[PDB]
Image (cartoon, coloured by chain):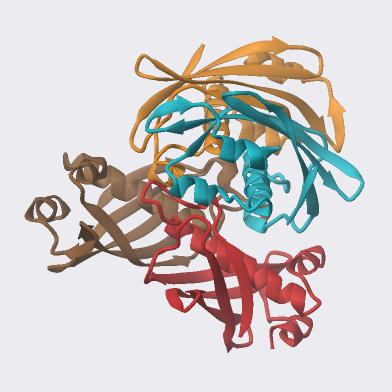
Chain colours: A red, B brown, C orange, D cyan
Amino acid sequence: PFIYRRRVQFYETDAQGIVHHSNYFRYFEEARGEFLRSKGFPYSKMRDMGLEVVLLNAYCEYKKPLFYDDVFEVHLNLEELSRFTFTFSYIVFKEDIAVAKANTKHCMVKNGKIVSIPKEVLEVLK
Amino acid sequence: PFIYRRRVQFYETDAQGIVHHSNYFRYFEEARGEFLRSKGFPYSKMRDMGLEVVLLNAYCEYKKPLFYDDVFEVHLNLEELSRFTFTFSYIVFKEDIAVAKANTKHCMVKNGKIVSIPKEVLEVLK
Amino acid sequence: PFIYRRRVQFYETDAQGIVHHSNYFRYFEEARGEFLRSKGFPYSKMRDMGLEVVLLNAYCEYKKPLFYDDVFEVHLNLEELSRFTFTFSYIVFKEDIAVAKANTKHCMVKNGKIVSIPKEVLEVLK
Amino acid sequence: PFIYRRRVQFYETDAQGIVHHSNYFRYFEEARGEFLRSKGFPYSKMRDMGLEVVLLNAYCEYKKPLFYDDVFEVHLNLEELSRFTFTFSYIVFKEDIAVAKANTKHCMVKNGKIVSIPKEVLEVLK
């Protein structure tokens, strides 16, 4: 897996004193961005080429909460890679504690149309 | 279903020109809140009584994007109701266009422990 | 003034149990959007014309907190209108209580350059 | 000054292709947090002791936009320190370009009342 380390910010919490569930998707985005960057092909460069990654679906299950100032790790793994789509899984740990498990599925678009995942992208996803 | 109507705000979009996927979960939260308020039992009243609803998992499938200033409707439906949990489904439409389909599963805690869903809550969920 | 009415959502709060200060700027945005819409010229239509409103500065002072489920009103007023800029003030009330006071200053851009505020926009700001 | 380094995330942008103005205040919060942590007194420790910092006002002037994937630095400086309040200033740079200049003013509360800033806090602010 690819490991992405992160500390919870105050604005990411809500009145329940935990990180709002919607923010977990933002953390997963950050992990995907760091993954691509680590492979030498950041998403920002794909966008410059006219490529868009489009989210098809997203799932998260929440096991234990994150609190303000918690340090956690997102373990990202490529789960599925087909002609037109790819799927990442995520496991969120705080130290030894499993906080959450998730996945997202994506496709790619160029010039308003769905395109087969380019070879240049397949090379970095793998 | 219960219908919640909402207009996309500029800050809810990202550089792709669409509503960021994480914001859909915020729209679903707003829908649930309005649903409970419509039954005469707002979540804020539950909280004041020391009850807390805990999200167990969330899933969203994205079909067509939402843009700035789009008016849309979330069709909220109770899908499951058991002794300890409940599940809502959501279908998002913009005019006639299916935008997204989602669900969330929840339980309830009081004094730091999982509790069976109070009869007072059961009566408003159904 | 123009009055914009709003209820606090759960995700707008933080662990302190109040609405995070950064969200007040989002509320002011919503008020400006509703103001323009009420005048028959929504910002979305300005954007379609290639116009961008650019924020120059923003100030907020916080007097009393907003809590989850509070209903409040933003009183928006046009404070300053010059050739290239305009300034709105905002006062946030919850019932009789003054919650916050703010202002924002803006200019306009078209085709990458600062432009005099168009007559078509001056007519709706006034 | 204290220097806080940060990369713009995709969800922090809006449809204009720039970082939404409200997110700048979130960056300033992150900077303050890191500053206190660097002094060996994180805000989370203050909170655990029952202290709360309260924002009184915030101001930001926007000079040049931030884009997705931009690396920037917030230069944080203590500007004022009195018996009951303190003020930070912030200058945001991306490479050599001044992006924004800001300030925030704060006080402290304990048991629901304004308190003079504890000597333990004074020692880390300075």
Q: How far across and down, in percent of the image, does residue D73 sit?
A: 79, 49
Q: How far across and down, in percent of the image, does residue D106 sit?
A: 58, 30
Name the quadrant of the N terminus of chain A.
bottom right
Tell me: B56 left or right of C91: left
Q: How far across and down, in percent of the image, does residue B71 sit?
A: 46, 43
Tell me: D23 left or right of C38: right
In the image, is residue B71 above or below residue C115?
below
Q: What residue sits 55% from the left and 28% below the top?
A: C28
In the image, is residue D108 above or below residue B98?
above
Asked whether D113 or D105 is in front, the reply is: D113
Asked whether A96 or B102 is in front, the reply is: A96
Q: What residue sits 40% from the left and 51% below the top?
A: A17
Q: Residue furthest right?
A: D96
Q: What residue sits 67% from the left and 39% below the top?
A: D125
Residue C53, can we see it?
no
Asked whether B93 or A59 is in front, the reply is: A59
In the image, is residue B34 above or below residue A85?
above
Image label count = 0
Asked whether C48 or B85 is in front, the reply is: B85
Name the quadrant of the C terminus of chain A.
bottom right
Q: Quadrant of residue B80?
A: bottom left
Residue D52, can we see it?
yes
Q: How far across and down, in percent of the image, does residue C102 sit?
A: 59, 21
